Image: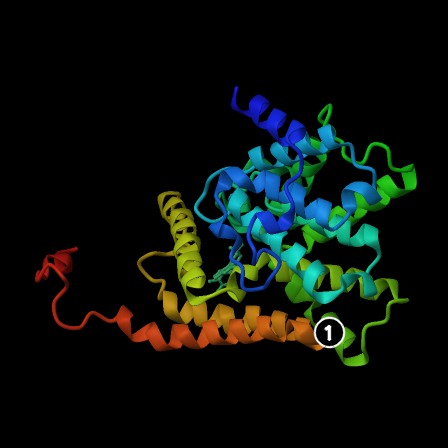
Amino acid sequence: SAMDDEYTKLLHDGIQPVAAIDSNFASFTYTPRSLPEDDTSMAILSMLQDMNFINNYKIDCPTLARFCLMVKKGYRDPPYHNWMHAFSVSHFCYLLYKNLELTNYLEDIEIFALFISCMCHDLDHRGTNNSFQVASKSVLAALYSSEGSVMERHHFAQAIAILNTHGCNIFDHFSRKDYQRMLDLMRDIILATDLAHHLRIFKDLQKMAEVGYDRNNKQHHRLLLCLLMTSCDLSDQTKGWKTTRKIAELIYKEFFSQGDLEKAMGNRPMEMMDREKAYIPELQISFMEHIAMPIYKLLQDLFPKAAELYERVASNREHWTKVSHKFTIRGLPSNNSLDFLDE
Ligand SMILES: Cc1cc([C@@H]2CN(C(=O)c3ccc(F)c(Br)c3)CC(F)(F)C2)n2ncnc2n1
Ligand SMILES: [Mg+2]
Ligand SMILES: [Zn+2]
């Protein structure tokens, strides 16, 4: 029984210090996906220890170890939306705490909720978007389509189910008020990961950055939590070209699988999910320019030490422009054949 021994070690051996994981672990240059998957549960505990959440909130270590394993095991294995995505999004949250002094802008309990929301925010993803849920009349649409953010509601609900599994409630000693505040935060933060939501609140984020962040304004807290969540969710784009290239591979595999299922059902997939129509370079450029860059630009406006993130993201965009031409076949293909043209 793989999990029982894994739990034993994670509990009885002790929490390893962050620096023993990698000398560079707490820097924006680090690529969390470099960490072997078998070490990631220990890494989560190490990050929580280093942020001092274990002691500040008196988390029971047996309960925590079970919780982390249950969360990990609650991800499936589609090419992009898997445990390694949630681990890396969680790691970026840790980066922001380390590098940007969040405690000057947010309450402790808010930062904690953000991190625990990053762990849980794609739980049980099936490699399909919200609209596929509605078009295929899945069980999840039956439960949630009338409210919208179908997958995100499912993710949150899976988080709650893990919490109400016996031995997994890391918050069960909180006051009733703090318990309710944590669950409410997790709902808002995980819901914020639907990009439709982000697009709706984009102007309100702009406004906040114009007038300047007001720590006494409760709506500013909520808006910032959303922006930070989105920043963690897309943080793959703040690393190096190699990571970006690889990540695009995983996303388009996942997207194109969806499109293949849609074609089988008689539907026309959106362009970016149709392997016969998607022109990856112009799609990435558009995504980078019209969604990702403005996010990290806002983050830079609010936190001057976040400049390097924006610049990476702009640099990754230009790189796509630069390699775009390689998607045109010049000469013959490697095999020296034009057989591919009767296909
Ligand atoms: C880190 C990262 C994450 C995502 C996607 C963004 N998402 C989209 O809907 C989407 C919207 C407009 C687009 F033009 C494209 Br393309 C995709 C949702 C998601 F699938 F969860 C994650 N991408 N996509 C392309 N490079 C990415 N890098
Ligand atoms: Mg998601
Ligand atoms: Zn995500």
Amino acid type, residue under disc 1 in the picture? Leu
| Rendered residue at 27%/71% (across/down) | 326
Pick the residue in front: 225 or 239.
239
Number of marks: 1
Q: Position of residue 202 (x, y in %)?
A: 68, 69
Question: Which residue is nearer to you in this view: 297 or 287?
Answer: 297
Colouring scheme, one of rainbow, by chain, secondary structure, one colour: rainbow
Q: Is residue 39 above or below residue 285?
A: above
Q: Quadrant of residue 166?
A: top right
Residue 77 in picture, x, y percent from top left: 47, 39
Observer-nearest of 89 and 189 = 89
Q: Secondary structure at mark 1?
A: helix
**Which residue occupies the foreground of this view, 235 or 2?**
2
Image point (84%, 56%), residue name = 107
Q: Could you tell me which residue is drawn at 62 percent across and 24 percent down?
A: 8
In the displayed orientation, state which residue is furthest to the top. Answer: 1
Q: Residue at x 36, y 62 (%)?
A: 278
The residue labelled by disc 1 is 302
Residue 23 appears at what percent x and percent y?
56, 56
Visible residue check, residue 145: no
Question: Vertically, is 244 above or below 163?
Answer: below
What residue occupies the far left of the structure in this picture? 336
Q: Position of residue 215 (x, y in %)?
A: 87, 67
Q: Quadrant of the C terminus?
A: bottom left
Residue 164 shown left or right of residue 296 in the figure: right
User: In the displayed structure, does residue 266 sit left or right of residue 134?
Assistant: left
**Alpha-carbon neighbours of circle 1 within 10 Å: few (<14), some, or many (≥20)?**
some
Does residue 17 appear anywhere in the picture? yes
Relative to 170, 4 lies left or right: left
